[PDB]
Length: 223
Ligand SMILES: N=C(N)c1ccc(O[C@H]2CO[C@H]3[C@@H]2OC[C@H]3Oc2cccc(C(=N)N)c2)cc1
Ligand SMILES: [Ca+2]
Image (cartoon, rainbow, N blue to C red; front, side):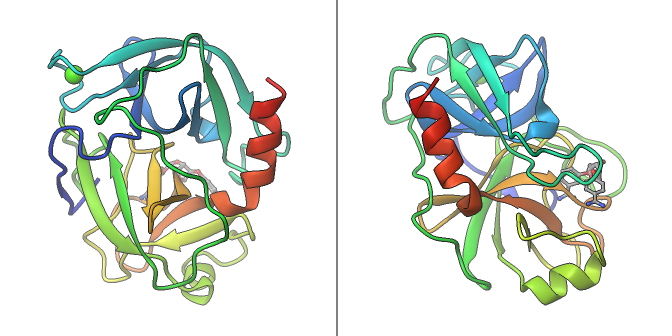
């Protein structure tokens, strides 16, 4: 997260870290057994880490649970990141508490200008590299589809939206991928892609979760 702030420990209790010996992507807990992330974060051997603030220090509210299965969206395209969403099942149910909590799925899509909260353990610099160990947060509005498509001609599908600030300075970044975009209490986006981080006229691009609620619900009920 570039241009954000320190969230405060466990104030985003649905935020998970995906760990394969090290943090490599964010995710969102959507019930006691399932996490939503980006398909481009797929790998084997995932451990889900819940209740995290400092991902390098055991602070006493963590739950580390291995994934028992992963399901990449059937139509995920790795070249374009169209349909950049995946579900991960926990081998055992998480113990839900005030620091480890699910986020609701949308009942409808969010409209432009709606404010959201984006969070993650990604790079905090727009040039060069610095990784925080505590969770970072950013408030950012959904941008109009026109501004989105203009910044990225021929690349935005109906499954993508942009959020952020055209002037630059504030964005998600590498290592934030898979993490949540929450607008009015609902998981409306997933950190997906962009151009650099926090560059002018290049806002972040996010998986449009509302389009996937039927697939999510049907997939978790059958697995
Ligand atoms: N539809 C396209 N033509 C497209 C889609 C994804 C794509 O993935 C690339 C570009 O962005 C991804 C990846 O390589 C770098 C990584 O950057 C990210 C990741 C996550 C967040 C951000 C951000 N600044 N908000 C940037 C490239 C082209
Ligand atoms: Ca920790």
